[PDB]
Image 1: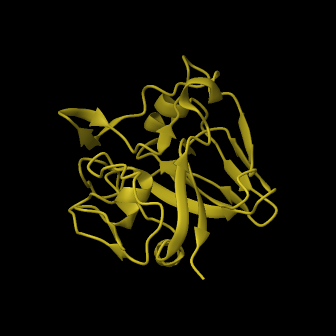
Image 2: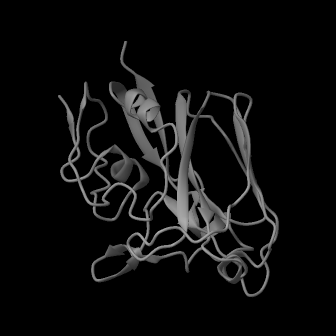
Length: 214
């Protein structure tokens, strides 16, 4: 039987847009039933990368589980994991954010080089998603990260990419002139994925272990 996403599309569901139920119930499905949404995919405006490929990857699944790949309370001792909410992603009358990601910002006036790895010991492919934040102004860049010229690197045995934030005033969407791009990759059993950043990384909180049908 199908995965019914109710009023969200795949983007909103997989990122954990507050408007979408985390829907951690169906562990297998043959197809996904999506619905549309002003934003209820990407409440914070930006581009979801490799999106069609993801939809395809998630189309037919024989097993599927969400797990806390990087526990919020213990993963980020040197960064602030509590301030990353936005009016663009409201929940219950207040600023919020995606459930499955954490918008890390500076602690005090410092943003140390972050370095976090995960080894896939799940016995199956793990889907990991993250975001890159592109602030609207250099002032906003400093206000969030404190470092002016930053990078993000994400790598595994199968994947390698360096990201550079692009600071610029985009057209206002849901009151945001900044943007957030969303990325993902599949980590093979036994492989390691590493994250490194001096700013601008919307880190994974929850990831997904899965097997595809036939």
